[PDB]
Image (cartoon, coloured by chain):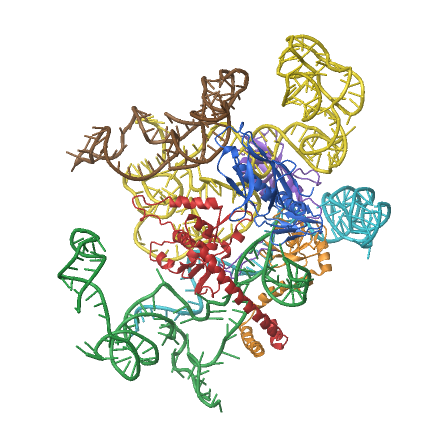
Chain colours: A red, B blue, C purple, D orange, E cyan, F yellow, G brown, H green
Amino acid sequence: SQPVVVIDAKDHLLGRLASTIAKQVLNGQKIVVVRAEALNISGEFFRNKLKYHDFLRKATAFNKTRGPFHFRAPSRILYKAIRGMVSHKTARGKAALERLKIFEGIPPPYDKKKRVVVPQALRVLRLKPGRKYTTLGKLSTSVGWKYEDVVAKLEDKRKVRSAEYYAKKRAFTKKVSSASAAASESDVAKQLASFGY
Amino acid sequence: MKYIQTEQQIEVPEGVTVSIKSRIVKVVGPRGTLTKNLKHIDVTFTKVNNQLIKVAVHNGGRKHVAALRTVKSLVDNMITGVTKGYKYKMRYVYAHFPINVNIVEKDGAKFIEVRNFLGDKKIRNVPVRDGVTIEFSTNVKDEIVLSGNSVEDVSQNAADLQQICRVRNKDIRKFLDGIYVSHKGFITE
Amino acid sequence: AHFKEYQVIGRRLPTESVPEPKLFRMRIFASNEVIAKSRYWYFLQKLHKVKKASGEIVSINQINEAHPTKVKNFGVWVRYDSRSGTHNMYKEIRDVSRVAAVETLYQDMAARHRARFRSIHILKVAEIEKTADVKRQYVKQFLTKDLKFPLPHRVQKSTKTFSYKRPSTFY
Amino acid sequence: STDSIVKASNWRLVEVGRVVLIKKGQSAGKLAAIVEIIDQKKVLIDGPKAGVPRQAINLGQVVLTPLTFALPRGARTATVSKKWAAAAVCEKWAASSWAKKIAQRERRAALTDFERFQVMVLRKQKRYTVKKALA
RNA sequence: GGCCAGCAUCAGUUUUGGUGGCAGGAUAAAUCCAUAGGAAUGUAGCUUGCCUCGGUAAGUAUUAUAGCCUGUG
RNA sequence: AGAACUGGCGAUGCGGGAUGAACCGAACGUAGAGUUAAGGUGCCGGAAUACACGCUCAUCAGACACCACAAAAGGUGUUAGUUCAUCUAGACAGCCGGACGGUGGCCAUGGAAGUCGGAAUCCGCUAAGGAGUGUGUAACAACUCACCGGCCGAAUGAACUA
RNA sequence: GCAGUCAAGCGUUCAUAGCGACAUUGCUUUUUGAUUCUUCGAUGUCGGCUCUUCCUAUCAUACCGAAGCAGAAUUCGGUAA
RNA sequence: UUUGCUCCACACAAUAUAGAUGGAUACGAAUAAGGCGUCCUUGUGGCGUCGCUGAACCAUAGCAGGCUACGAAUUGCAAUGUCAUUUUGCGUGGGGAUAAAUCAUUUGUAUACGACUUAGA
């Protein structure tokens, strides 16, 4: 409903995100997907690795600069999955895939802006407990990514800079609840409680 | 078939306190202290006494339950190693060429090097894990004793030894040389 | 399907040499009173020299369950045609109704042996009156004093597509 | 030794006598009580006090309510209505925040526009006092 | 006075809902009421090592200081 | 390659099988509303990330007949099942104890008490202990266990089916 | 052309270390054949030279396992092109 | 030759929109486990409590929103009924800064031509 949506992608499944994204973005919603190195995927690591090494195998023989561009970053693996789900070869798929902005980690603009979660793709809800799942950062790194040890050095600064905000806010609102709980014993609230507020 | 409840139980001799929170075991004792991670298993834990603990799995279905008793043994081995401790007595064997073993402080931690493994010149070194103390028998000067609390460290180090002191490109039915474990026990009994 | 249990009474057509031809009863499980008759003539034509055109259906009534709010442990003798040869089986089912047991038979047979409704004949269905002649663990485990088990990993279904807090599986 | 801090989880668990709340059916929302257990995935129930029949049902169609009352295995409707009324389960239930929020939703939804305007007026009084106080 | 839209009253085709009356079936089965027996995933009661009001132990006990099943009406 | 009956393509578009002369559905005047076929409803893709009982996790999974392939033989990987059975007069798993004597039962005699080895077969003790299952000293010993018991207090092996 | 399954036997004793008959299941299209759909208003037709790439059913090289492997030397097999 | 150029301040005009007309409202991590409040022998602590949907939370009255510390009809029974935000120009007036590249010539660490590399008041 909001003009722009910010999707935390931790504990998510890739192809079950992308079928929601690829429709919500084709229907006119701007989406950004953030913390994509924390994505999750079905299947064991060796298996989902071979399913990439049998992709790197596929390159145009007479000149491989014409052929399938095997991207190694999670932000681009997800974009691959979505580009497949979208008719990117038209001005509708094109127009949609410019409504999307995918990142690794959470940059500042989407740092101080609320994040959400797609429940019909959370590994927690969907997958059986006991199944093996593979993490996209480990995968990308094993197929030739480079910037894993950076994202962890930045997102941690994000986290310690955010935890202090949360503590500030909590140690502000614990008194708002007290001074509005100290004000709920009047007719103004005994009457609202009958209306359902 | 999917069962309903398969539960094992873990006795606890005194002096021990077993702290769990989010499937992270921590055990203490006279000998020392230890920890373990079991996030990769679905399993519960309850405290009916300070004298024992009850571990449980629910429907499972013949795969979770085989890890149930496994976990039970792992925790039990852990308690055993932080109450008594583990002792692995390896021994040397050879025909002509002795094996000259010693401990050495390299740039980092301790190592244990062996020379004259069948006349070889390759001084083959082995790291010592952190949880291990280490010595030589004295009643007979042709053994070695690894020791500690964690069996999965002690035994892994002993195997790390006897896997590198293994002859290659020769008849093993004849070249029964190297070092090998001989006794597994404790350092209290 | 939404099986209903029928009571089918049929009869060879009455000729002068025997105008009281002896009647034959079958207790059939079917989705309706059209295929009930079909299965009657199917199983009868397997035992007695009679067809539809050489017979008539006297009665098709329904048998509604008497104590459908009483949990029971049925035992089910059955034969089934595999891809290579027939076999007989015995399976025990815990349910309230003699026909719900059959619904959950055809399914756990179509899964465990990939047998269709056409490759299955229900020989005998009957309660085990006492909880000591059961022979199967997948029933006997629910026959325990003071049963109680949890549902560990709960999943709350979303109506909307976006949520603003991580969901929680606790029950 | 020192007391062993051991804690895993304290589930509400399907048992005989447990109370449940039905989410998806003809008798949606209406409370009931489990009687006995058919298998892992389904049970039977009887809520007589609220007008629920004696059903056999799965556990997706319901929710497990924490509260619980004592009864024997396989009990009947009269017996269940006996025990329900003894324990005063609807009183233990309406006390809770769960039913309070449920009723609150059901009441917010049933508001005329007049009520929805009265609310806007009234909240412009409470917040005035609260913003005066948090100063 | 002509074109374009809106509403109503109607007509044809069709879609989607709320509600009532009736008939049948084992003149539904059931639940419920009554009643005759039976047993345990054995309730009280009584034996039973100590003890939380017999909590445990396991014998007895067939509704009793819970209940259930079956049959008939 | 060649015949029989029918239906089709040819001469035929249309919705479906991604695509396809023949398959499934169905046969065409131009248009509008409604309903369906066959096929399908995660997204591309219009339509349930619907409900229900289960099976499967594959270091070449598998996924719309025609159709674009796959076998014999195997697997305690798992699920369900069939037929035997042993057995609370305590089997089977697991440790603890004994396993002795008549007697080296005769010969191969360079040496075999059981045993590098060939003919040959029974008593005493008992809970039970092979005139011998293994290790092997020129031979003797000493060990092993099938034969029995203590804990044990549960049930269990064997074959087969799909 | 290649491989597999039973395994009667060879194998000083020892089916299967290695091989392995009588039978039997398949794979391949680098053979030869059968067929005749395309091409007869033309697809330049043997071999070699040159040059690149691919396949594995690996001759060698790397790490391993198994032998009737003492060593040495050999054979069988595996991951691997 | 402040004809020129560059800003910001407002006055109009002009061109375009992959599409807002209340608010994109911020902890982290686990899920066979956690959030919040308190006490504290500050611990993987004791107690209580919440979830079981954001159906929330916040804002929300006034000429399409006014005068003073009253006016609002007659868009005549509906006909977006005009506000969003980039890019361009015109002039008005208050400032601010005063250049390089290419051709041609040339060198050869370069070169098929272009290109590259160098030098030149």
Which part of the image, by quadrant, shows the C terminus of chain A? Answer: bottom right
Q: Is residue A24 visible?
A: yes
**Residue H47 place in picture, x, y as percent:** 68, 62
For residue H21, side relative to residue A62 (left or right): right
The correct choice, above or below, for C115 with respect to D4 in the image is above
**Residue D121 place in picture, x, y as percent:** 55, 77
**Residue B129 place in picture, x, y as percent:** 56, 46
**Residue A122 place in picture, x, y as percent:** 51, 54
Q: Quadrant of residue A23?
A: bottom left
Please tell me which residue lies in front, A97 or C147: A97
Q: Quadrant of residue D133?
A: bottom right
Please tell me which residue lies in front, D72 or C157: C157
Q: Is residue C106 visible?
A: no
The correct choice, above or below, for A112 with respect to E41 in the image is below
Residue name at image x 62 percent, y 77 percent: A187
For residue B161, side relative to residue H39 (left or right): left
Residue name at image x 39 percent, y 60 percent: A99
For residue E50, side relative to residue B163 (left or right): right
The correct choice, above or below, for F127 with respect to B9 in the image is above
Residue name at image x 53 percent, y 66 percent: A164
Q: Quadrant of residue F125?
A: top right
The correct choice, above or below, for F98 with respect to F42 in the image is above
Report the label total: 0
Please tell me which residue lies in front, F59 or C114: F59
